Length: 230
Length: 228
Length: 8
Ligand code: NA
Image (cartoon, rainbow over all chains, first blue to last red; front, side):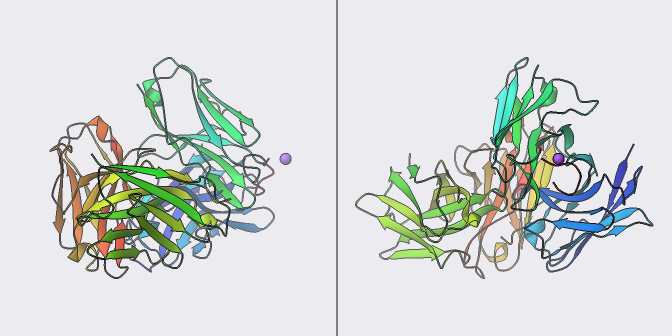
């Protein structure tokens, strides 16, 4: 099993620097199959990928368009950890910050998250809300373009309030062990679908679609769909 | 009784002009007590006040700093409607656009919203949670330039729906809003309280004020409230 | 995602 332990301040003054540290256990930070990401989440900015560092015979760094000029993600091979540094923070940077492991384009392992407050094309298209009655088959759609969905894998996540997103679907239609076969995924052209058969009250959560955009050179998330069981 | 009808193109080519109209009925565009606003909600930036127009024996036009060089709100008394003219659009202008009436600074009546595709100081906690019946509070930190010297407004927003007015004038509650909701303002801080939380309150809550340094309407980052 | 041997 692999666990990630997050550390950092819960408050940063404006124009100051936010520093977060993510400790790794059960895996190496220099893993040829792994990538170490930072993701934040807020009602205004939604589920926003920040950046990542990874080792492919050398250390690489991929940063998001929104925070590229202010972000730095450094790995520490001795302590076996990686950090997040965001300069000149402003109230917009107020969000819940997560560190996560990418292994096949999928963010399979997440940290518990750190709430950070600051005080004195770009997004895939999902329906804001979906609903259904118990026992039904409910499908959540996501429309993108050739730059993202049309050329890259599609991933789905299930997020219960106050907890990091859980990997539901990887590689368009593949399913991790542990996830019941009620959840299925599909992809055709520039669109994707997440289907839930035998809908239960347990399935009440926020569902996110995720892919990669070549024009943005980074991980792209959907707006997220709130599923309500009637 | 007042209804705002929104209309306009959904997809706009870059370097072109976005034209959005807001049809008014049940009220007059020349109303001396009303203001006519435009607000957009970026999928990655959130609520963003664009500008307003109003008439007080003279037409007025207030615009946000970040759009002032290319925004214009045109009133039309003969048609009784006002439009949004956003010129030289960029992919950054892709958002859900709302038109809303301003009364005493309060955005009490909103339009349906128009998703437009082109192909800031207030501080709130990111998320909040409560169990049905529990009293929960949502705070907002500002400064002397906004909350410290101006009224505070509160809004509730469900997915795919325009924000709904909850509290105006720091702690005044409009009719239609249950007594469960209340607000207060302490110095440069404001707070929304939900005494006797119910399951129907699961939404995003936004705090609104007015900044003098930006000389425009300012929104908060919003707080996601979860009912357990 | 070109970061891996896993994309498209
Ligand atoms: Na391949």
